[PDB]
Amino acid sequence: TQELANFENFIGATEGFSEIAYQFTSHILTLGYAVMLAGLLYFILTIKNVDKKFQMSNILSAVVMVSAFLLLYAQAQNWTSSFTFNEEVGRYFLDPSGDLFNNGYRYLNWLIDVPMLLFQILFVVSLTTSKFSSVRNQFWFSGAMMIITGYIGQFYEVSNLTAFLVWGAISSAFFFHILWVMKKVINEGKEGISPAGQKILSNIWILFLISWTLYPGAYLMPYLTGVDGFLYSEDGVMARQLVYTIADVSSKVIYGVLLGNLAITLSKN
Ligand SMILES: *C/C=C(C)/C=C/C=C(C)/C=C/C1=C(C)CCCC1(C)C
Ligand code: NA
């Protein structure tokens, strides 16, 4: 029995991490929060560039950046605090005098950010036949549920793969519903805007679809080559944390930038 849970800790306690793996992950997580702070300033500075009626979107972007910056900063500190060099072996191992790697930071970020990200498109596009309040409530419920059930799942990642995957499947149910509602919102948003605006919404959809699907990918990452597999290792920890960071930048900053551009193109008409 290996007291330690979560996958980063398990690897850290048994295998350890190479200098490369440890340093790379550290730098990736740092770039994570660096990009959010630059984003925060961007959304603040450019708020004036869009008409009053759209500005709640820029605002929500900014607030997402605040939470993303704070919690990803915490996550990065959590990484370097949690693993420590052994001279004998020449790898980084779980430090028992540290606090242990904790996914809580990222998952809290998700609980806060997912509702706002879904919400903020409703202040740029106009629905047609759907009700603002119906779409909102559906986003908020399914979003909360998606993150909550995921978080439950993630506890069993090492200890009970069955629970890990089942909770993850439930989570994916809510995910699918979100995709379905977002697609409706984007299709309705395309009616009665310039072709320029339609083109940007097409790109938002693609970005949204790819970026949000990275998260379940990273969730599953360690297991995507079986238990004997090359990913079931520091390389899976590396890839998971890399993909989470690519997702965060794309789902928050690039998403936000695209919505801003759409808002500007809408005023032009
Ligand atoms: C800015 C952060 C965002 C947009 C986070 C999004 C997170 C997800 C879409 C998570 C989805 C998950 C599943 C669909 C299954 C596995 C558990 C999750 C929470 C990773
Ligand atoms: Na350390």
Image (spheres, rainbow, N blue to C red):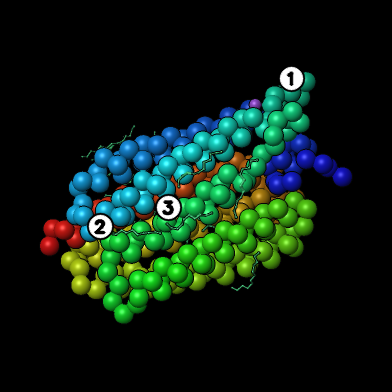
Q: Amino acid at mark 3?
A: Ser
Find numbered disc 1 in the image and state the secondary structure of the residue it sits on.
loop
Left or right: 16 with respect to 126? right
Mark 2 surroundings within 10 Å by alpha-carbon count, few (fewer than 14), some (14 through 19), many (20 or more): many
Q: Amino acid at mark 1?
A: Glu
Rendered residue at 42%/52% (across/down): 251
Rendered residue at 61%/54% (across/down): 219
Residue that numbered label 3 is attached to? 251
Residue 23 showing in the rendered view: yes
Residues 65 and 214: in front is 65
Q: Amino acid at mark 2?
A: Phe
Mark 1 surroundings within 10 Å by alpha-carbon count, few (fewer than 14), some (14 through 19), many (20 or more): few
Quick one: quadrant of the C terminus?
bottom left
Q: Say which label, 1 or 3, has the lower sequence index.
A: 1
User: In this picture, is 254 found above or below 196?
Assistant: above
Q: Which mark is residue 54?
A: 2
User: In this picture, is 206 found above or below 242?
Assistant: below
Disc 1 vs disc 3: which is toward the camera? 3
Left or right: 102 with respect to 189? right
Residue lying farthest left?
Answer: 269
Quick one: quadrant of the N terminus?
top right
Rendered residue at 41%/68% (across/down): 136
Disc 3 vs disc 2: which is toward the camera? 2
Q: CA distance from mark 1 to mark 3?
A: 40 Å
Q: CA distance from mark 1 to mark 2?
A: 56 Å
Left or right: 196 with respect to 108? left
Whether the residue carrying mark 3 lies under 8 Å from ligand 1 is answered with: yes
Residue that numbered label 1 is attached to? 87
Find numbered disc 2 in the image and state the secondary structure of the residue it sits on.
helix
